[PDB]
Image 1: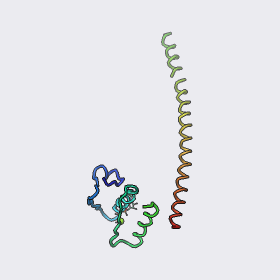
Image 2: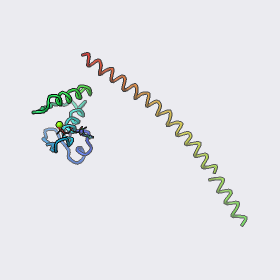
Image 3: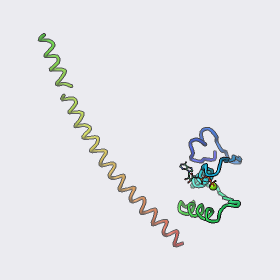
Image 4: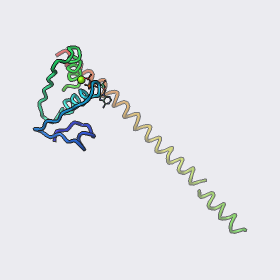
Length: 73
Length: 61
Ligand SMILES: Nc1ncnc2c1ncn2[C@@H]1O[C@H](COP(=O)(O)OP(=O)(O)OP(=O)(O)O)[C@@H](O)[C@H]1O
Ligand SMILES: [Mg+2]
């Protein structure tokens, strides 16, 4: 299992290690929050996380990094 | 007629007393709940401060 902590994902759309699940939505639909939540949720699951931010606003990328740092992620 | 009033009074008092006994018990549960909640709030407050001090130290790092 690769746990997201989202009951809607981990019950009905399960994501497993070695998988590729796409997160698709409209602008401001909550896509980043779902992905970020997943990385924050792997706190003691011993996985490594990479967050590639292609073409994303510099301030926005900084905000994500700050959020990760506060959590200890 | 006699057997009715007595029953009403018997049943009735069994019930007022019972209701107030339940009140007491709750007065007990709430009393318990209040203590637990208070302790939990203190611990939670402790949580916040402790963890934010940790965050500070990490910032210093
Ligand atoms: N489970 C949730 N509960 C409440 N709010 C949420 C949840 N998930 C996301 N949001 C909110 O939705 C807003 C937009 O979310 P987010 O930026 O994560 O989505 P997005 O699709 O990446 O948007 P963008 O296209 O701007 O990148 C955020 O402010 C976030 O707080
Ligand atoms: Mg986004």
